[PDB]
């Protein structure tokens, strides 16, 4: 199923050299405020079942470590040239068949919107049940699932302000409590750094895939922020492999510092409160000291969710509905069916219990990492066609538009990762990056792997007055 007479527009357009504005410091800032999200509190919470609170600080920095290792390779395409993830997805898969992951992956950002509005509730409802003792989880889930949709079309700077300041404001509060908890549970960081592991069983191998598969979504598609990084049009195999690692570590000094802290304060609220649930362990810790504040601590989680959320979870599935189903939704109806869609997945309970298995789920998406890197790196040796990636009939159209051997490789890749269960991701990424070269040298039969109109790549990025 594809659709005929297709149009490729300014939203997906490539970033030029006269637009880039993200230097490795400022990209290191979008990785600090990016290690700060409730997906991480909780992951590091439930870990305390099988390992102590230091082991999780070792697995934490361990995830992010393998995560910068994939970041390096993946980021490269985007920085060099300046493209969406929506745009680069078209290399291993077709230009009409690149939508298989572009969709499977725009369904995550919705899931992380259900799971995120769900704390908007816990926080809107904790502030009103500690004010009126009445509790309505699902009313708030819907009042919040309405507010977003409105401030989506007509948002003012007042939310924007809240963006950058939010992650830090919560990292500040998120440690302060750890003072509070280590002060009332009368334990020292030294006693606390060893209180988990009263139910060993899970392998550490699986303990690292967790924090891996938490980032996978952001890593596979960094293309979307990376395409604003100062890059040099006049640098070589050296000057451009040095800016690759300059960024690739500009990111590791933002994500592993910050997300070893939310990893901690989250395993601390567990083996020190009992609650992986932020909002709950929050009201419970600061309201067991100040309920004039436990309400200001839940007025925060509410306000900081109410600016983070939309940006990173609702915008993308919105613009994919007007793209993949043009005559069907508006920006006003894409936004609204997006909301309804996420809410209706019922995320929060999936997490709560086996979030450990939704992060071994969002980590069985390794073959896509191995497939995309193998392509921009091993199969096309960094040679790409800016002109063919923007035309219905290009050398990436393959079988009418879908690359069937790239979906096949992904499939062989998965089945070979069930031959190694505690190291799946590591063996689903290794298997797909080695098995994509052959399938691309087999299409190197039915299709060219390059074009002679590619000498125009520089025509797309250098300013045109």
Image: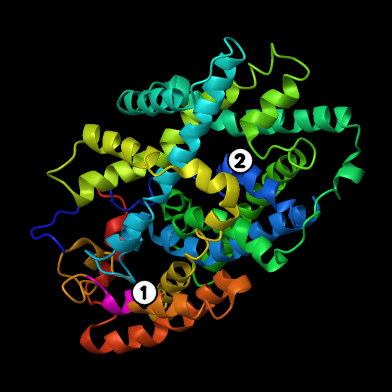
Report the residue that reaches farthest toward the left. 5
Q: Whole-percent x and y of residue 319?
A: 28, 43
Say whether residue 252 is magenta. no
Residue labelled with disc 2: 36
| Residue 340 makes an appearance in the image | yes
Q: In this view, does 46 lie to the left or right of 74?
A: right
Q: Give 281 or 22, whichever is nearer the viewer.
A: 281
Whether residue 140 is situated above or below residue 330 in the rendered picture: above
- Give the total of numbered labels: 2
Name the quarter where the N terminus is drawn.
Answer: bottom left
State the image quarter where residue 199 is shown: bottom right
Name the quarter where the C terminus is drawn.
Answer: top left
Local secondary structure at mark 1: loop
Say whether residue 406 is magenta. yes
State the image quarter where residue 334 is shown: top left
Q: Whole-percent x and y of residue 335?
A: 29, 35
Whether residue 112 is situated above or below residue 289 in the rendered picture: below
**Residues shaded magenta:** 402-407
Q: Whole-percent x and y of residue 356?
A: 60, 55
Q: Is residue 187 left or right of residue 164?
A: right
The residue depicted at 33 percent of the width and 41 percent of the height is 341
The residue depicted at 46 percent of the width and 75 percent of the height is 414
Instruction: Please identify the dominant SS of the magenta region.
Output: helix
The residue depicted at 14 percent of the width and 54 percent of the height is 7
Q: Give 24 or 263, whichever is nearer the viewer.
A: 263
The residue depicted at 85 percent of the width and 48 percent of the height is 193
The colour scheme used here is rainbow
Q: Give 91 or 274, whichever is nearer the viewer.
A: 274
Q: Give 95 or 141, whichever is nearer the viewer.
A: 141
Residue labelled with disc 1: 383
């Amino acid at each position: 199923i594809e659709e005929a007479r297709s149009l490729l527009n300014p939203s997906n357009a490539p970033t030029r050299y006269a637009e880039r504005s993200v230097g490795p410091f400022s990209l290191a800032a979008i990785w600090f405020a990016m290690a700060i999200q409730v997906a991480i509190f909780i992951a590091a919470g439930q870990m305390t079942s099988s390992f102590q609170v230091w082991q999780v600080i070792v697995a934490i920095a361990a995830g992010c470590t393998i995560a910068v290792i994939l970041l390096f390779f993946t980021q490269s395409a985007a920085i060099r040239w300046g493209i969406n993830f929506t745009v680069a997805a078209r290399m291993p898969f077709g230009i009409r068949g690149s939508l298989i992951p572009i969709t499977l992956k725009a369904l995550l950002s919705l899931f992380w919107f259900g799971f995120q509005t769900w704390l908007g509730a816990l926080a809107l409802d904790e502030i009103t049940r500690l004010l009126t003792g009445f509790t309505n989880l699902p009313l708030w889930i819907v009042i919040f699932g309405a507010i977003q949709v409105v401030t989506t079309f007509y948002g003012i700077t007042f939310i924007r302000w809240m963006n950058v300041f939010a992650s830090p404001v919560l990292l500040a509060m998120g440690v302060y409590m750890v003072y509070l908890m280590l002060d009332g549970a009368d334990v020292s960081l030294g006693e606390v750094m060893s209180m988990g592991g009263e139910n060993p069983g899970m392998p550490f191998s699986t303990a690292i895939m967790i924090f891996v598969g938490g980032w996978i979504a952001v890593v596979v598609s960094i293309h979307d922020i990376v395409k604003e990084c100062k890059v040099d049009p006049n640098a070589s195999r050296e000057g451009q492999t040095k800016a690759d690692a300059r960024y690739a570590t500009a990111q590791w000094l933002g994500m592993v510092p910050a997300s070893i802290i939310f990893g901690f304060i989250g395993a601390a609220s567990m083996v020190l409160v009992g609650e992986w649930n932020p909002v709950i362990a929050i009201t419970e810790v600061v309201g067991g000291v100040s309920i004039p504040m436990a309400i200001l601590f839940q007025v925060f989680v509410l306000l900081a969710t109410w600016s983070t959320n939309p940006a990173a979870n609702l915008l993308s599935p919105a613009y994919t509905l007007c793209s993949t189903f043009p005559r069907v939704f508006t920006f006003k109806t894409g936004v609204i069916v997006s909301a309804v869609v996420g809410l209706l997945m019922m995320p929060w309970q999936f997490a709560g219990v086996l979030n450990t298995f939704l992060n071994l789920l969002a980590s069985a998406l390794g073959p896509l990492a191995g497939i995309m890197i193998s392509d921009y790196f091993l199969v096309r040796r960094r040679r790409i066609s800016l002109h063919d990636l923007y035309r219905t009939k290009g050398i990436y159209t393959y079988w009418r538009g879908v690359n069937w051997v790239a979906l096949a490789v992904y499939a062989v890749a998965l089945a070979v990762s069930f031959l190694t269960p505690d190291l799946m991701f590591v063996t689903g990424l290794i298997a797909a990056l080695l098995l994509h070269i052959p399938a691309m040298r087999w299409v190197a039969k039915t299709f060219p792997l390059f074009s002679e109109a590619e000498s125009r790549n520089e025509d797309y990025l250098r300013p045109i007055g």
